[PDB]
């Protein structure tokens, strides 16, 4: 069929008609952003030449290639720690939440740390359950328990002190009064909050409950992060499967070439495997540089979303 | 260094860049944000700063009642910038790394001229002096293929690095529009604090913003209330 | 006469264990839902190799003959099961129509209620045999569903095969060079397959 | 590290100087239990043989061969080859083991050796120098003939039929007397499958039925089907094998390897360094197991500080005071209980104007590379070959020119946001 772009709506305009909203809903729209790749480094001599001395000598004729590949992947790897740190480490001190939870009826228990669990929140545990040859994977600098201490500090500052923990030292303020500032920050007179406080708290608590239900009912929400995990695994499996390719050589098993032929003919056949595996590794590193630039744009966006949306109240529409 | 590699001058000389940072700065000082929105309108700097205090929700009288102090804190903080920049090069790690990445890329591209790629020599005149045409073409094809692959590697990494530098130039252009020509309300966009103003200073391959920010200090605890009863009616601030 | 192959005639393509994984391979396979010639026999072509099966409760089908001529001029396979042991030999044999039951040489070797199924192929001079056995209910046609055939014999005898015949309910189909996707379970048995050329969903 | 950076000064940091790779402690070979050896007793130990001037050959196939014993056998007083030596033949395999055996006068048998000469090698028992193997002979005057002479023997294709019944006599020496001999030439007929003991849990080089590699062989819970010999991971990589002499399954782990990173303060500050063996276990290499790898030459510390040199998995290292490199779990910052309650607010009574510097790059060094001069160095002979690659050099000049013009635009978009050159008052 020819697609519909949406329901047709003649807006009821006239020079003297206005529509004013008599009520609201607190929405809690989840947004999900990539921040870091799987940090990787490839021992390109062990990838290309498989710990063969006869091949390893031929790879020296190519000079700096199997060294600027490591410098490129090391630049990407250090950049993943920078991306992760630019996003989460926007906080000077690890703020912690009081023992009592007198937040005016708002219920953060599903997003605050669970000490019975790493000490992640309930929703962070759903999010962590939903996502699922010379190549080496390197750990992030911040462990998942350190990332959870930063999201805890950001969240505990955000709850107990508003935007103030971004602009200076965290200044405590009651959460009903912080939300009364958030209402003025959208041009809604703050008595609208205090007069509807139980209703607004219930709409927030219920909207948080719908996040748990949504994240339990479908994996499709985390498509962005699962796509990043899938692209990393697809790239690494493609890079490994390319070791099985001939590139015109007598065999893709380097020990066959070194046993089926005299050394003069073997060097020509090995140089096809070196050329093909080196082109394969250059192709992988080039794709990872372009993909790391995409993830860095997403990490700079996530870092900006944390500065404006978490540490502040952005007036930037959508 | 002669090997077809050439460095071209920028269109703007560092003196022309310094005339632009001078013009941006002289506009910013004498006229506030107005020189971005139209013609520069003069305004006294103690009145521009009271508009800039009012733009972070700090009432104008907080500047005038503290003008000597606020001026001394700005002058002293500019002194700490001179002392920091005079003391250590480590502040400019971003710009000196951009210079290093390009120098390492060019030195890698030059050192790759010495690589054999499977040819009898990496010196092209050795091949052409030692070998007759039909043999020489086979060795020169290896050098052409290797040097061409080395130059495609260089240009690919320079295209990706130019996209990174353009993302930074678009960010610097946005910081100049919003932090210099205006007062950004975007939290932590113009330095950590409630932003007042910023001054561009030129630097080789880059720009430096001196983000003047109000940072609050010396807080006291108080009892607080959302609203206050009077004649049975609730009052809100 | 003919019957539908359904998903029958898949076999373990190589001597490799794989588990909980899907492997895509191109080999001489019986194509899914192809038509299989039914017999109750004459000399037949061998083509790119053969799937052979019989619905049984009696053991009347005892063996096979293969070659170019299947007679005198060149080395020709005789394969027989006699319930004492399997016999294989490759002589320049001579007989009547066959040495069937009335109820030079270069190599030799020794080793309805049910279906017996087999595959016969020849690559790089390796003549290969696979088999499987299962109980059945239907007598008229090959049973629906899936169970992969597993190797029995793998001989470097180097003979050229273009014809074959059976030695005395039985079915013959031809293998074709096709991509299949094979599903290996947790124990490394093949439990399902896709003929990639069958339909757009299989592609 | 100095050599890795091509520098005599090293700045503070962590540098991947090398790759650690556990070497194979020894080499395994496994093949199936040796069987189906060709019955050469029918050649050398049987009670009779054909007359050598009328002999014929036959081919062994689908078999092993006793050539490793034959290379040191007492069954001949003499031997010779037209092919490779018998010690090489015992290490090889062929399409078939073509061979023949016969009785002759000793010198007439020698006149039919592979690559020899005489009416035997010419026609009675042919022996061209192209014969793909070896032959052997010994005296036999007690058994190769009667008391009346070599009537059981003969004299004059390879190893097959000027010939007549032999003139040898039982009273003669080994050249003139009756003798027994055989000859052969060269897949389906192979030398024996010599196999080692098995070695679990060490890193070893291995051969299993012609699969080869370096790994740690481990006993395993995998259940291969009776016809399966090897196991493979998702991306083709072999991850188990059946031992061909005792049919249990060995799981193969790679020999441990990883980046070696040197952690250093600047060479201004010290010559002392610590070494991280990334992802390696300290049992395989002060010593400290981090989650990032084994760390050597740094002190594990229970305090926490800001991250100076990043090791990974929450660990950082730094140089501290009497001085050493320490390693510690990084401090994310001091913890703070914000003094929250439903009626407490903190209000700042003062401020600091903070002039936070921010530094942004804006333009690269504008480069253009003349790709004909870079690739071909003002050689005409090279430049004509570079034309066969077509548009590539023009496309590279276009790409670098796009980057170069873009640096002027990047610089223009940052600074030229002001329409007029404003000036400051006196
Ligand atoms: C905050 O909300 C959570 C659920 O989002 C409430 O926790 C549940 O409370 C009921 C009744 O005590 C228990 O049966 C459930 O097992 C609890 N669920 C979990 C996941 O703990 C919690 O009681 C609310 N807190 C307040 C103060 O209202
Ligand atoms: C504003 O809208 C909310 C729903 O978003 C209304 O709240 C519901 O009110 C009905 C009774 O009228 C209850 O059954 C529901 O349980 C309430 N929902 C929630 C989330 O509390 C509210 O009544 C509306 N207010 C006005 C003045 O129109
Ligand atoms: C080729 C061959 O079978 N040679 C055998 C030899 O191995 C054995 O040792 C001997 C009896 O001692 O008889 C002969
Ligand atoms: C506010 O009061 C609490 C005790 O009620 C104290 O712990 C906290 O340090 C005080 N904060 C400031 C900024 O004075
Ligand atoms: C061959 O098989 C198809 C189903 O795959 C069937 O439609 C067709 O009729 C068969 N042909 C014959 C001759 O039976
Ligand atoms: C059956 O075959 C075996 C060899 O597999 C042979 O020894 C036996 O004599 C045969 N018996 C009959 C009755 O053919
Ligand atoms: C066997 O082969 C020989 C030639 O090697 C030939 O003379 C003979 O006729 C053949 N006999 C049969 C039955 O094939
Ligand atoms: C088999 O066929 C090939 C050509 O396809 C031929 O070279 C070879 O000699 C043949 N071998 C036999 C045993 O018929
Ligand atoms: C695997 O095989 C064993 C018997 O060898 C059987 O008990 C088990 O149920 C099988 N498991 C699966 C997943 O097929
Ligand atoms: C190999 O021989 C040994 C005895 O030498 C025996 O214990 C082992 O079971 C045999 N293995 C096979 C696979 O036959
Ligand atoms: C290292 O020494 C040089 C002089 O040799 C000095 O200029 C530089 O500032 C020193 N740096 C550090 C971090 O000590
Ligand atoms: C490998 O490292 C772990 C700690 O990560 C340690 O418990 C174990 O003993 C090490 N392995 C060996 C064989 O020592
Ligand atoms: C450091 O921590 C370990 C336990 O992790 C403990 O045994 C040791 O006594 C501690 N030492 C100091 C100086 O805190
Ligand atoms: C505010 O802070 C400054 C130092 O930043 C200090 O000199 C001044 O006396 C303080 N003023 C008050 C009212 O506390």
Image (cartoon, coloured by chain):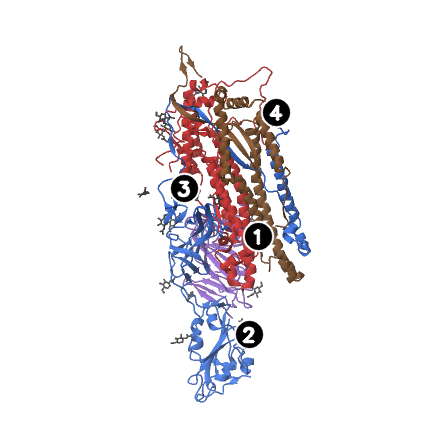
Chain colours: A red, B brown, C purple, D blue
Callout 4: chain: B
Q: Say if mark 4 contacts mark 2, CB within 8 Å.
A: no
Farthest-out residue, front: D426
Q: Are marks 2 and 3 in contact (CB under 8 Å)?
A: no
* On screen, residue A115 above or below C198: above
Q: Is mark 1 within 8 Å of ligand 11?
A: no
Identify the chain of the residue marked 2, using the numbered disc in the image.
D
Residue that badge 1 annotates: B111
Image quarter for residue D408?
A: top right
Q: Are marks 4 and 1 on the same chain?
A: yes
Q: Nearer the viewer, residue D273 or C13?
A: D273
- Mark 4 sits on what residue? B40
Where A315 falls versus D268 (above or below)?
Answer: above
Circles 4 and 3 on the same chain: no
Q: In the displayed structure, does residue A36 sit left or right of residue B4?
A: left
Label 4 sits on a secondary structure element that is loop
Marks 4 and 2 belong to one chain: no
Are the two marked residues, 4 and 1, in contact with CB atoms closer than 8 angstroms? no
Q: Nearer the viewer, mark 2 or mark 3?
A: 3
Label 4 beta carbon within 8 A of ligand 14: no
Write down the chain letter for disc 1.
Answer: B
The label on residue D314 is 3
For label 4, the crowd category at 10 Å Cα-Cα, with few meaning under 14, some 14 to 19 and many 20 or more, is some
């Amino acid at each position: 069929y020819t697609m519909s772009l949406g329901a047709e709506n003649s807006v009821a305009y006239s020079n003297n008609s206005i529509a004013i909203p008599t009520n609201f809903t607190i929405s809690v729209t989840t947004e999900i952003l990539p921040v870091s790749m799987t940090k990787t480094s490839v021992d390109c001599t062990m990838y290309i030449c498989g710990d063969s001395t006869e091949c390893s000598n031929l790879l020296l004729q190519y000079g700096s290639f199997c060294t600027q590949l490591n410098r490129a992947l090391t630049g990407i790897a250090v950049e993943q720690d920078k991306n992760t740190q630019e996003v989460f480490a926007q906080v000077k001190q690890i703020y912690k939440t009081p023992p009592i939870k007198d937040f005016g009826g708002f219920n953060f228990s599903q997003i605050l740390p669970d000490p019975s669990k790493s000490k992640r929140s309930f929703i962070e545990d759903l999010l962590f359950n939903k996502v699922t040859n010379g190549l080496t994977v390197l750990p992030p600098l911040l462990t998942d328990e350190m990332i959870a201490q930063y999201t805890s500090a950001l969240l505990a500052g955000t709850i107990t002190s508003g935007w103030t923990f971004g602009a200076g030292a965290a200044l405590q303020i009651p959460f009903a009064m912080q939300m009364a500032y958030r209402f003025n920050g959208i041009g809604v007179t703050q008595n609208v909050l205090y007069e509807n406080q139980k209703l607004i708290a219930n709409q927030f608590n219920s909207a948080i409950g719908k996040i748990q239900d949504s994240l339990s009912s479908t994996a499709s929400a985390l498509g962005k992060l699962q796509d990043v995990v899938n692209q990393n695994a697809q790239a690494l499996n493609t890079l490994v499967k390319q070791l099985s390719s001939n590139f015109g050589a007598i065999s893709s098993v380097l020990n066959d070439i070194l046993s089926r032929l005299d050394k003069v003919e073997a060097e020509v056949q090995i140089d096809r495997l070196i050329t093909g595996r080196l082109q394969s590794l250059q192709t992988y590193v080039t794709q990872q540089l372009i993909r790391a630039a995409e993830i860095r744009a997403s990490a700079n966006l996530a870092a900006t979303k944390m500065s404006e949306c978490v540490l502040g109240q952005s007036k930037r529409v959508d | 260094k002669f090997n077809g590699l050439t460095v071209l001058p920028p269109l703007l000389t560092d003196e022309m860049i310094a005339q632009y940072t001078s013009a941006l700065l002289a506009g910013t000082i004498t006229s506030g944000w107005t020189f971005g929105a139209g013609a520069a309108l003069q305004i006294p700097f103690a009145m521009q700063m009271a508009y800039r205090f009012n733009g972070i929700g700090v009432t104008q009288n907080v500047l005038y009642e503290n003008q000597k102090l606020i001026a001394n804190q700005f002058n002293s903080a500019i002194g700490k910038i001179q002392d920091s920049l005079s003391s250590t090069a480590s502040a400019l790690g971003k710009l000196q790394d951009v210079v290093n990445q390009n120098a390492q890329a060019l030195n890698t591209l030059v050192k790759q001229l010495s690589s054999n790629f499977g040819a009898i020599s990496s010196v092209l005149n050795d091949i052409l002096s030692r070998l007759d045409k039909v043999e020489a073409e086979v060795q020169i094809d290896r050098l052409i293929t290797g040097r061409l692959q080395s130059l495609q590697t260089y240009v690919t990494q320079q295209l990706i690095r130019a996209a990174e530098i353009r993302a930074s130039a678009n960010l610097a252009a946005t910081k100049m529009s919003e932090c210099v020509l205006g007062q950004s309300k975007r939290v932590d966009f113009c330095g950590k604090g409630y932003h007042l103003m910023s001054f561009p200073q030129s630097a080789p391959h880059g720009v430096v913003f001196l983000h003047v920010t109000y940072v609050p200090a010396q807080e006291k605890n108080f009892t607080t209330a959302p609203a206050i009863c009077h004649d049975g009616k609730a009052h809100f601030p | 006469a003919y019957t539908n192959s359904f998903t029958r005639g898949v076999y373990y393509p190589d001597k490799v264990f794989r588990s909980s994984v899907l492997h895509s391979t191109q080999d001489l396979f019986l194509p899914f839902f192809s038509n299989v010639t039914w017999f109750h026999n004459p000399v037949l072509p061998f083509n790119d190799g053969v799937y052979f099966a019989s619905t049984e409760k009696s053991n009347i089908i005892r063996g096979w003959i293969f070659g170019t001529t299947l007679d005198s001029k060149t080395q020709s396979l005789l394969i027989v099961n006699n319930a004492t042991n399997v016999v294989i030999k490759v002589c320049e044999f001579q007989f009547c129509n066959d040495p069937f039951l009335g109820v030079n040489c270069t190599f030799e070797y020794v080793s309805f209620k049910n279906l017996r199924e087999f595959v016969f192929k020849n690559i790089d001079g390796y003549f290969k045999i696979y088999s499987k056995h299962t109980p059945i209910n239907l007598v008229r046609d090959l049973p629906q569903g899936f169970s992969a055939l597993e190797p029995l014999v793998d001989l470097p005898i180097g003979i050229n095969i273009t014809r074959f015949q059976t030695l005395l309910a039985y079915y013959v189909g031809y293998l074709q060079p096709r991509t299949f996707l094979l599903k290996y379970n947790e124990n490394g048995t093949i439990t399902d397959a896709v003929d990639c050329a069958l339909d757009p969903l299989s592609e | 590290t100095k050599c890795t950076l091509k520098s005599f000064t090293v700045e503070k940091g962590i540098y991947q100087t090398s790759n650690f790779r556990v070497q194979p402690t020894e080499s395994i070979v496994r093949f199936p239990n040796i069987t189906n050896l060709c019955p050469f007793g029918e050649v050398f130990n049987a009670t009779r043989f054909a007359s050598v001037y009328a002999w014929n050959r036959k081919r062994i196939s689908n078999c092993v061969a006793d050539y490793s014993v034959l290379y040191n056998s007492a069954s001949f007083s003499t031997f010779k080859c037209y092919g490779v030596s018998p010690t090489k033949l015992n290490d090889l395999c062929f399409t078939n083991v073509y061979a023949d055996s016969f009785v002759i006068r000793g010198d007439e048998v020698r006149q039919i050796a592979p690559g020899q000469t005489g009416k035997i090698a010419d026609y009675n028992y042919k022996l061209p120098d192209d014969f793909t193997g070896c032959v052997i002979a010994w005296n036999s005057n007690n058994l190769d003939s009667k008391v009346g002479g070599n009537y059981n023997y003969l004299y004059r294709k390879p190893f097959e039929r000027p010939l007549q019944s032999y003139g040898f006599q039982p009273t003669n020496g080994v050249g003139y007397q009756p003798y027994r001999v055989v000859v052969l030439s060269f897949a389906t007929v192979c030398g024996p499958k010599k196999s080692t003991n098995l070695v679990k849990n060490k890193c070893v080089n291995f051969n299993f039925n012609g699969l080869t590699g370096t790994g740690v062989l481990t006993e395993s819970n995998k259940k291969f089907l009776p016809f399966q010999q090897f196991g493979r991971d998702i991306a083709d990589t072999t991850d188990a094998v059946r031992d061909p002499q005792t049919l249990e399954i060995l799981d193969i782990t790679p020999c441990s390897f990883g980046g070696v990173s040197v952690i250093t303060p600047g060479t201004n500050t010290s010559n002392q360094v610590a070494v991280l063996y990334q992802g390696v276990n300290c049992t395989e290499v002060n010593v400290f197991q981090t989650r990032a790898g084994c760390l050597i030459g740094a002190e594990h510390v229970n305090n926490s500080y800001e991250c100076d040199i990043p090791i990974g998995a929450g660990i950082c290292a730094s140089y501290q005071t009497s001085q050493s490199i320490i390693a510690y779990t990084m401090s994310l910052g001091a913890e703070n209980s914000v003094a929250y309650s439903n009626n407490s607010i903190a209000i700042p009574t003062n401020f600091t104007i903070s002039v936070t510097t921010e530094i942004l790059p804006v333009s690269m060094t504008k480069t253009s590379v003349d790709c004909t001069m870079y690739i071909c160095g003002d050689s005409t002979e090279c430049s004509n070959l570079l034309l066969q690659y077509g548009s590539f050099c023009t496309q590279l000049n276009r790409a670098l020119t796009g980057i170069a013009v873009e640096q002027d635009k990047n610089t223009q978009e940052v600074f030229a946001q002001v329409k007029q050159i404003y000036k400051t008052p006196p």
